[PDB]
Image (cartoon, each protein chain N blue to C red):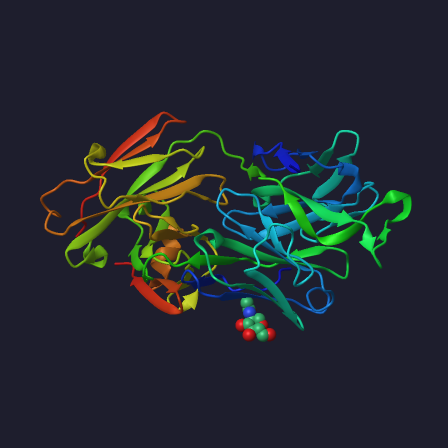
Length: 239
Length: 212
Ligand SMILES: *[C@@H]1O[C@H](CO)[C@@H](O)[C@H](O)[C@H]1NC(C)=O
């Protein structure tokens, strides 16, 4: 029942400061080394820093040195990560991981380090669920909706693909429906992307019969409840 | 810096699969301190293997670790549905740092493999009139959920202004992804063609659009 619970994450503006926390339970915190590991969206695990049991030895990755500071409060069972001047590229999930440790065994004899200290085992045995940091300068903004018109290039014999480009919005929840909900078959709304701007963009596509192009009208119903914007756009084929 | 892993490894239930992890003499080749982590969607990572070949308590005998020179390997025998996820190798550094690999998506095949359907949309005239331009590449119905997307302006590749999503399930259990190439209306009209090149399971699809 060893646990690690991260907090402090959310939406923060670039150039600002931010303190992340990680509360440990179910083990004696001061006996172990602790790490911070980040994961940028759709990317791999990336080691940030390690702090010794006593908080006297600190190691930081070269990509994070100068930006972040690791600390711990052995009286409060807490780990910290302090940011000075955040950058839009710092956007990631931050995981708190315990460094595995204990005595070294030799001929069925337990050996400890000076002052009953544990030796590091060189693996992370307990992990938290993470806290997400989203660095963006943006304020509430409604989307721009553009048609992704069907043509020969989007026609796969019998059917045809058409969509809606939902550009430059903030914050995250955008909803897309087709023909006021009357069309659900063949609909896919892709996850949003977070551009260098600090704004999100997304696409929604629908597969329809090629016969209907010219007769049936297709409309995407875009919903941005945070900006109270609703956009109904008719995607029709071009010439 | 990062240890090198294949992006995707797949197999049928019961099969045996292997994940490689390439490092150097200052990490993988330097110590017997290679650990492996499994990350299931919505779940915290968990240690599978440590110190090259050792298993923690509660980890199945089906997971085994090995090392040869600067290369470490994780083997999964009798592949199970619950082994699906991303696998990361890690190593201790000669600087007392930790280095992780890029990760490997492990798919336990539950349906036949499908190559992607690629639809490339040029910027709409509405967008061009708004002094913006976006090329939209839609990648759908592929399985397993791992693709590589590359853009070309004429025949030369373009890395600036590219944003690609991570594949997600498209309700019918297949995966979909999208990639965008943001340009100024001027850049769009300055080149003869633009291409979206998608690689899945060693096979490639390339669609081309031209300012017309
Ligand atoms: C790593 O190196 C080995 C041999 O040293 C090779 O066979 C393998 O394809 C490589 N793996 C990656 C992910 O580059």
